[PDB]
Amino acid sequence: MFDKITSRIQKLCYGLNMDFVDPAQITMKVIQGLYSGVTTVELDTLAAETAATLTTKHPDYAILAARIAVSNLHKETKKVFSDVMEDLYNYINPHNGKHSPMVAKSTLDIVLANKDRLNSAIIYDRDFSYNYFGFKTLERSYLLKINGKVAERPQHMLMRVSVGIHKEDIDAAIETYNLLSERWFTHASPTLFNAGTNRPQLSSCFLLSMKDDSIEGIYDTLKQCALISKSAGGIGVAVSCIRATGSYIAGTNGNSNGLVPMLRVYNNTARYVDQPGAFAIYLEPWHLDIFEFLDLKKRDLFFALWIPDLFMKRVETNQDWSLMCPNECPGLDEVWGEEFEKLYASYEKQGRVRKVVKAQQLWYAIIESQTETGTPYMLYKDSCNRKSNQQNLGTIKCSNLCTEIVEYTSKDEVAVCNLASLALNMYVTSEHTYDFKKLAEVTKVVVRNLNKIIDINYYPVPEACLSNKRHRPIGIGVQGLADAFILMRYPFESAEAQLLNKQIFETIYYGALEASCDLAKEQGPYETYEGSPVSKGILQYDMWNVTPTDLWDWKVLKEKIAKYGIRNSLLIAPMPTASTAQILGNNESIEPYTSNIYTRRVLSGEFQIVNPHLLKDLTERGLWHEEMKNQIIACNGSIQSIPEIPDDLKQLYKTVWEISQKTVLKMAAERGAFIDQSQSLNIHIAEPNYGKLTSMHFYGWKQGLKTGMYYLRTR
Amino acid sequence: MHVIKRDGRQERVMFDKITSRIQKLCYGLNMDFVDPAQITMKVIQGLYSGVTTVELDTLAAETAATLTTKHPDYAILAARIAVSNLHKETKKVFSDVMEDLYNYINPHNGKHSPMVAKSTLDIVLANKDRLNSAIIYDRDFSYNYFGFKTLERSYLLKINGKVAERPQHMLMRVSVGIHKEDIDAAIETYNLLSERWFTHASPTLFNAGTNRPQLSSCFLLSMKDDSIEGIYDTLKQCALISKSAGGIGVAVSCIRATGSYIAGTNGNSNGLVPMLRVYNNTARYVDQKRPGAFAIYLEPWHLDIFEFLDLKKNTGKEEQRARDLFFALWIPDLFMKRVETNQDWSLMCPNECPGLDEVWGEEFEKLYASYEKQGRVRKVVKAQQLWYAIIESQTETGTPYMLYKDSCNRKSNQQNLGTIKCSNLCTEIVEYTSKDEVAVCNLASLALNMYVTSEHTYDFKKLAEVTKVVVRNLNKIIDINYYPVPEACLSNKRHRPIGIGVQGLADAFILMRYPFESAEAQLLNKQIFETIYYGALEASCDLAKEQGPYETYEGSPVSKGILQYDMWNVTPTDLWDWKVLKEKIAKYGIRNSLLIAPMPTASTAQILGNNESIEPYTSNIYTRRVGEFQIVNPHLLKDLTERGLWHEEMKNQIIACNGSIQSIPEIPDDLKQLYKTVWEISQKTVLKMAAERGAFIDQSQSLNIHIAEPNYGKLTSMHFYGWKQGLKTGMYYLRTR
Ligand SMILES: Nc1ncnc2c1ncn2[C@H]1C[C@H](O)[C@@H](COP(=O)(O)OP(=O)(O)OP(=O)(O)O)O1
Ligand SMILES: Cc1cn([C@H]2C[C@H](O)[C@@H](COP(=O)(O)OP(=O)(O)OP(=O)(O)O)O2)c(=O)[nH]c1=O
Ligand SMILES: Cc1cn([C@H]2C[C@H](O)[C@@H](COP(=O)(O)OP(=O)(O)OP(=O)(O)O)O2)c(=O)[nH]c1=O
Ligand SMILES: [Mg+2]
Ligand SMILES: [Mg+2]
């Protein structure tokens, strides 16, 4: 009897490690929610659930689990792509009666005029390549649904995005289709949510100079934020030009209440417009309201600092910092580095300061905020501007929400970003050699994609659109760096890892540029190209004084770029990639495993998950048991103190806490020479003291990092 | 013992010189109850040796005012002492003070900051001659201590602490500020202000003849529409107007309901409540020591009304509160009919049910029904339920104000423009607003007790002439005001509305010796307001001749010879020939769509010494805080002191009685009659009187209701009464106790 269930679980067991997967186990839990009443479709989830719990015994359960629920999706959705599309278009909302197409006619009509070539391109066996928690992610949000029931299979949705990008160009579409569905990279969420629809808001982040220091200013800027958040976008906002508390107002002959009351207005605007807000506010440490600033998360806004070098210099030489009001001392954010230290001091040597503190004391109020709340983020204004390819445009006033994007912004330019990410774990061949020829190749495609995205994209406000058209900046990231190192057999901190880290990024960048060049050959450079460091032969690694390894002939590439230029002001920026890395079963971005154990909620409750790579070594060596697992939870996810585990692995699966943050910082410093934008650097300090922190910032600062620190994590 | 004189010159104490100086300022005062040796005695104890001769003026004017409780003359005397001080501390010649104020260099910020406009100076200056000798400083001695200290606290200009302006220099600046090179009229206005016949609204008082003049107090807005973009555009406007110290009232009914579908995002609308948080947050943050004030107007067919209703509570949950906005209801006739006949009432989304707010009266009644019929409703409730909800809101908070859309639109001369979607912060202004037009209003009030004579007869003929003047002034303001936003300016030049108000109405009855509630008082109330409407139309007519109609005149009720009182079916008394005027208009047209708008004269009433607006006394005994002082109704005290009926315990037995004189066995009834508090008076009678005067007020009236012990019965009956009277504003605040 339960035999009829088992022999059916078994069907989807192909290629799985049957030392550790045992279908009999599931059946024993499933056969009990059985009765004369419901049957198969119900029991289908039942088993998927059960299987999914069992992930703790073996990673293959996640995959088995996945497969079952997938089988069941297929058993309840249309096969033919064009036919699924047809339904999404037609959907009359039978609620009111008005027609509401879920895809866009043009994408429909493109799809139908090639129903032949697109339909038979889709390989639906590719829906089994996702793990459970990955699949469930898609099913919650990424797969389009008519009234309850999901319509799109994951292939459908990929094909949709693909043609949603390459429109009339089928070839480019089917090659993007493949790449994606084999999980060689991914687009940003907005792209996957929106490509092929009526509101194709694909970009994924915006930046924003505060238009002007008046009510009129503050409220136009506010109108804009509301508008971007409407159509999804995250925002960075440059706020430093707003006059401080006490600063006189001529028009009303009153006295301004300063930056904070104004940050309340914005906060409140984020609680409103949603589809929760998310603004990063960037303040410069010379602003007279910087102290109140540091108490605010100490609320729907994240604070970040636009640090000028001068400030770091003064802090380390126990010194005199002078807080100014931007009304009283104009243009202080319109300038960086040299011209800043001249202009700033000029105001100091002119008396015109509102209040002097010791540099060191401000510093320590920062360390206080970070230990409390994990914020403010630390970004170095001078580093960012010095190594920016957009420096010919002016002074770069701030960054995006996750500190990775560094772009110019003005009264009439609001910077945007279009992002995507390469799955580094996919390029390590089954020989523990890393395939770079293939990595470069895929980047070049991602560039063409992102580049196409600029023109088709829906822009929420006009100067988002004006910005992006002038400088055509893109942003390309990575995920699974950690899994790459593990699949290679490399302790994250090993010299072996440390080289690979450079090499990977020498490659991503080589390809990006090379592809950006071919596009410039094809359609000319972006119009604010000539004037920039690349018209001058100075690529990103030069600005760092790094000479790359002989892996690629940059000699040859520079001669190309000298001939036809590039298409995009900027290209690379490794980002958090939180939501996508969940689908692909990867560790987020460039960071180690925070723990070797963690959970994940899925509708009702959670599932307990051990590091997939890890569990596979412990079980094969027959070291996996009850209390074995129960102990690692006791050690917050480390295995260092568990006695019967080899030397080999204790090294291989060190958690981020057990890793040297100095080393982490140094490694970013390395790769960051081939990242033309910035990177989202979290810092993990187990037991913090103000000492450890202070050298951290200082170490990373000395390394010359564009972003010093995204989040500080403490416990 | 000695006193330091006005020059550092030690002078021994000589207490007769105090009494002597006081006596010098008792011209015209009834000396039988004003013993000025009483102050002397009370001064020379609160008095150490070496104290400044200037402090023996403050200490003395302070003492003098705490004796209002003996004879109101004392309160006038207390001022006289403070003014006889100020004059000594001030430059006499007007044109000199104007020089200082301009040439004033900011002693902190080394740069320069005029306090008058260059033009205002260059006029005053090139007109030194006439203007200087025009001013009568013997008018500064005609206020009482309380009016005076309000003036002193914000209405005269301070050069670095030191009050530069004398009250006449102020009055004068304002006149030139309105009249520029028109020196004949500046002087005529100065005379009518300084003789206390009327007062301009505070924003005019403040800014008149300064640079970038914010002369107007009130602004009306309609939301820009169901959009994140509309919302934030209307918010920038509100911010911009609030920075210019302007009061605001807003039409918010078009906004999607909590739940309503949002196309572009597939998500769903969070409703009015969340948006109103954003409006509170902005009101808090933009200013004018004073936070901006928005009145929010909702129509009772909107799905979010119940939430709208608990938002003013100080009891509930932090997330759904907004104690900084003021809530109002724009009420269709239908809702009221539905209530008194226990029928159901449907709540809609303006998204699934467009056009509701852009249409009134039967046009509405038709459109609303055909939605109900169509099943276009999100929730359907018993009408009485909503009405119960409304009246506990009022019981707990005193809000929402109660406006009747159908009255306002039916009886408005802006009718030819479209639907009037809301009123203002104070509910007396009834003007049109659109995507392109924010209605400003410019206001002033007449001191209604100035026009009653020694022989207890009223001077309507004079009241009509003063009104004419005001209209000419309020008109010029429109052309000199600096508009916070362009749509404000658009509107005002298009329809040139003006709102003329009143203060000292209850004072007017008392001088004649009328109870508020008599046939006498109730005839005069009609007659007075006829007079104001008559005089004002006649003024606007003259201007039309001089200049042309207001652009949007043609097709209006007036351009058809329909005057406000026509819209009520009320024949005026025979006091004035309304057919002569009607003939005069159909000739030249008028210059201002709207004219009369009885607003609540909050602080200009404190100055002129008058009782607020259209209202009877709240008490015969009260407080004004400046030490806070113990004023007895000046009128009452006179009749008591005259009839030799005033002492310590009587003053007290009234405080015992919450300022009522009713129970006191020693007072003639015809006095107990005249001096009833508002908590004695019939509110129905109040509502009838407004309605009765309402036929002559082309806008509305801020109208509080006082009900002592309030229940559902009393609150309900009171609204419905006024409603059936044809009132546009049926209730401003509900005050209780
Ligand atoms: N010798 C005195 N003894 C008591 N009170 C005095 C004396 N001199 C003046 N005062 C009081 C009377 C008034 O209430 C108050 C202000 O009167 P005022 O005559 O303006 O002061 P003053 O005498 O210092 O100046 P002035 O030089 O103009 O006379 O001072
Ligand atoms: C008027 C006003 C301004 N502000 C703020 C907003 C701005 O940051 C700052 C003044 O900017 P503005 O609003 O532009 O004031 P202004 O142009 O009339 O005066 P000035 O030219 O001297 O700057 O103060 C308030 O917080 N509350 C207010 O009521
Ligand atoms: C987009 C968005 C709209 N809204 C509300 C506010 C507005 O009253 C209402 C109108 O939506 P809009 O802001 O105009 O968005 P839309 O253009 O998609 O609207 P429409 O469906 O008419 O095309 O939606 C939010 O509260 N939060 C949001 O994030
Ligand atoms: Mg300004
Ligand atoms: Mg819309």
Image (tube, coloured by chain):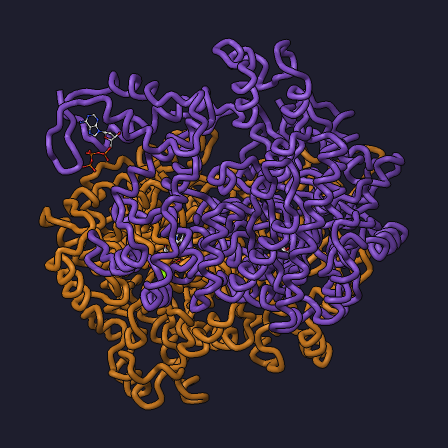
Chain colours: A orange, B purple
Residue positioned 58% across, 48% down in the render: B275
Res B664 quadrant in image: top right
Residue B449 on image: x %, y %: 58, 39
Numbered disc total: 0
Q: Is residue B280 visible?
A: yes
| Residue visible at 73% across and 23% down in the picture | B711
In the picture, which quadrant includes the C terminus of chain B? top right
Q: Is residue B325 above or below residue A212?
A: above
Whether residue A213 sits left or right of residue A694 in the image: it is: right
Image quarter for residue A406?
Answer: bottom left
Going by the picture, which residue comes out furthest to the front? B455
Residues A255 and A188: in front is: A255
The answer to which quarter of the image holds residue A527 is bottom left
Do we see residue A80 in this rendering?
no
- Assign the N terminus of chain B to one quadrant of the image: top left
Q: Position of residue B212 (x, y in %)?
A: 41, 62
In this view of the protein, which residue sits in the foreground, B142 or B432? B142
| Side (left or right) of B397 relative to A522 | right
- Using residue A681 as the reference point, say whether residue B11 is left or right of it: left
Residue in the foreground of this view, choosing between B696 and B105: B696
**x, y (%) of residue B58?**
29, 30
Q: Residue at x 74, y 58 (%)?
A: B358
Which is nearer the eye, A171 or B610?
B610
Q: Position of residue A380 (x, y in %)?
A: 25, 58
**Image point (71%, 35%), residue name:** B521
Q: Is residue B691 left or right of residue B285?
A: right
